[PDB]
Length: 296
DNA sequence: GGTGTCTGCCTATTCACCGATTTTG
DNA sequence: CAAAATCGGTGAATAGGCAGACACC
Ligand SMILES: [Ca+2]
Ligand SMILES: [Ca+2]
Image 1 (tube, rainbow, N blue to C red):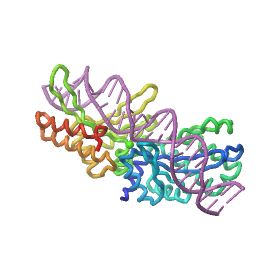
Image 2 (cartoon, rainbow, N blue to C red):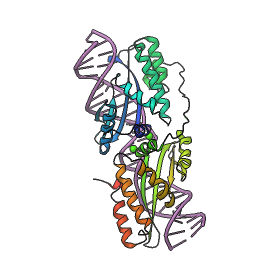
Image 3 (cartoon, chains in turn green, yellow, purple):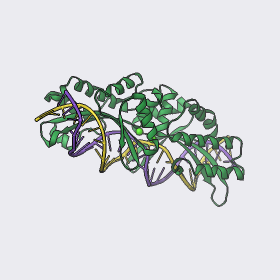
Image 4 (tube, chains in turn green, blue, yellow):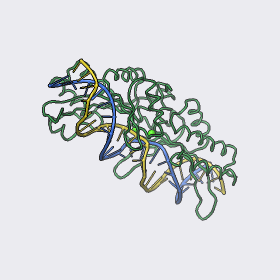
């Protein structure tokens, strides 16, 4: 019930969020309410993860995000110390670290209770401007000053495989590809491991090829949006390098079940039963019940 | 009677996921 | 030939967010 600290950090870099909110109290101008919060949104299927986090930090409350999503939110200021203490001993790796540093800075402003002053609000506004989506339209109208939006870029290395397990449990992918040969009935099995991330962490993505000794970064795109995908398709790399890593460092959530099914198919290929008409039908049945196909 | 804490509810997109074709040893 | 590399997607679980009730200093 108490997830490993480095697995938790890796998952946080994938799903976590450090939020600084600045709003008007009772729709009154020149009177701003400021508050900090940490939150992680997951599908209802992985609500157990959020509860495991809730047992590790002993803070936060889980509520419904939507009809298919729950979210763990830490809104108590005193409880935010638990979050800060954690990420000081197990630091973030992605560009979210920059958000955390800005998050901690706002914490100090609020801890000194300077957020109840004019100059304190002006400081938090400048902090929020570099956090996440930055200042909204209404906030930008209230503070038309040329505030710096940019932040110092984060360039860190993977601390350990325990972090990687948490990060992969969040953004990894274990897929089975049935390359159906056209003009025939024969189908070949290819295993597919993937880790997707925005282009803003390109440096960290490229390090995956070295840290795992395999795979290649694929620059993918949708409309005008772009991201990267670390992909391993060679069975030797998957069976000898990829799989043993996540056998050592266990995954969390429903994706663990996909990995277990993923290894079950790997064993069949390892025994060359994937070429068997019987073994392929078995693979076809396993594939149908993993990932998006999994309904139970 | 102000501020902090909590929750219902929302939107844009960064993901996870997908089948298939072409290249290579 | 079978595997590996490569292509070309896209629905949605995300990653942040908006607004206000209200317990409490
Ligand atoms: Ca992410
Ligand atoms: Ca995820």
